[PDB]
Amino acid sequence: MEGCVSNLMVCNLAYSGKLEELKESILADKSLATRTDQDSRTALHWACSAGHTEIVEFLLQLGVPVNDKDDAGWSPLHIAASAGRDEIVKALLGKGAQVNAVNQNGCTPLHYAASKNRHEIAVMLLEGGANPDAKDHYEATAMHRAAAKGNLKMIHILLYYKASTNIQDTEGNTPLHLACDEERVEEAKLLVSQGASIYIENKEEKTPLQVAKGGLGLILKRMVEG
């Protein structure tokens, strides 16, 4: 757990926060700065997941790769934003890091950021080149995950940057469908009044209104074209 990880001295060094040992290691060895192992990870990936900004900065300054996608671990900015690491997320971006790189399930930074409450972190990545309406394998969106468990603030920024277009998962699941299911009156009222087609049916051919609450749907559907 502590000290090292499993393999690759550079990976664990950044993980345990041994910048001195990491610097002397890369200084002495150039290949070590990129050398990958275990899961094709890089010390940046390990440092970002932990927090050690000094290690990621030192590696970044040298000109280490950042746009590189791991065997699944997404990009550096991906891991940084995911745990709400402002220092790491800013620090990776400064190096022209990626923005839409896909982990394995394509859960872009938006998808991960939305999963959290880091409203500010999500906005930073969006302007950097984060697909606001990008879909994953299941065609799920950050809006869906947030609408199911997030905040109204996210809705303000997401819509501000122009994101979400009634997207529907492979089996059916739009911003209103999930929001309605969550008994979220405010989220449903704002999303519908913004551009959430109520008629959009579901697996059972059910529209957000019908799944809203039988009657509650009448109010949401009326605003759309009552």
Image (cartoon, helix red, strand yellow):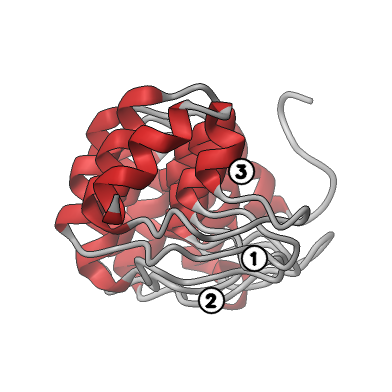
User: Of all residues shown, which one is farthest toward the left?
Assistant: 160
Q: Residue at x 61, y 77 (%)?
A: 31
Locate residue 36 relative to residue 174 in the image: left or right: right
Whether the residues at callouts 1 and 2 have beta carbons within 8 Å, the answer is no
Other residues around mark 1 within 10 Å, as few (<14) / some (14–19) / many (≥20): some
Residue position marked by numbered label 2 in the rendering? 30
Vertical arrangement, residue 134 with respect to residue 56, above or below: below
Of label 1 and label 3, which has the lower sequence position?
Answer: 3
Q: What type is the residue that disc 3 sits on?
A: Leu
Q: Position of residue 90 (x, y in %)?
A: 25, 51
Q: Position of residue 126 (x, y in %)?
A: 27, 62
Residue position marked by numbered label 1 in the rendering? 103
Residue position marked by numbered label 3 in the rendering? 13
Secondary structure, mark 1, is loop
Residue 124 visible here? yes
In 3D space, how far apart are the residues under numbered discs 1 and 3 (Cα atoms)?
23 Å
Q: Residue at x 67, y 69 (%)?
A: 70
Q: Would you identify the image quadrant in which residue 211 lies? A: top right
Please tell me the numbered disc located at residue 165: none
Q: Position of residue 50 (x, y in %)?
A: 54, 35
Vertical arrangement, residue 142 with respect to residue 155, above or below: below
In 3D space, how far apart are the residues under numbered discs 1 and 2 (Cα atoms)?
26 Å
Q: What type is the residue that disc 1 sits on?
A: Asn
Other residues around mark 2 within 10 Å, as few (<14) / some (14–19) / many (≥20): few
Of label 1 and label 2, which has the lower sequence position?
Answer: 2
